[PDB]
Image 1 (cartoon, rainbow, N blue to C red):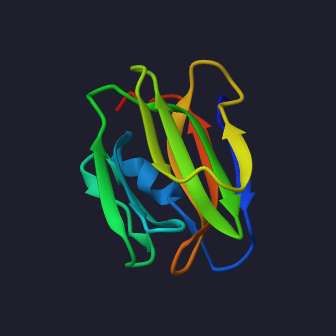
Image 2: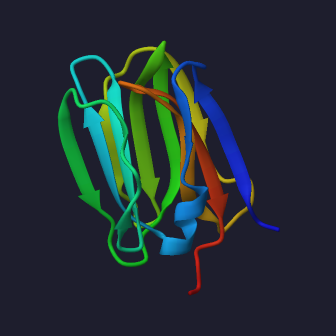
Image 3: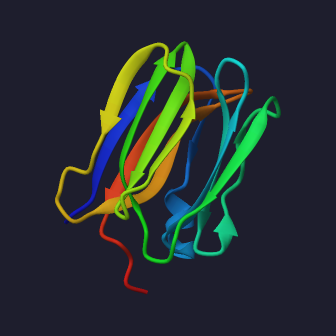
Length: 142
């Protein structure tokens, strides 16, 4: 009853992906974002102890952030122009995790219902991240 969805932010190219099935592996516990000179290139998210299937390209440097136990994302903002250019993940331990460059159209995603967190992502990808959507729900008890 508490789930919500923000998106889809970006353009309509590439191939759809969704981490809806990965929810069963656990809460989000880590993020990988690949970034090149121009764009957000790729994404991988750890659900419990299991990484999602990587989406995006091979170009660029990877950044890997491990969330603390019980830390979740409660806001995702960013920018896109043709493809995703910037992503900012804000956590409920007060951390701001920023990736990419400030150029393009801005978006800001927050959960519709209070006391919910980022449970999974979806979007579109190819050699880059074309679009992103954020799926919010209660933090998992089991």
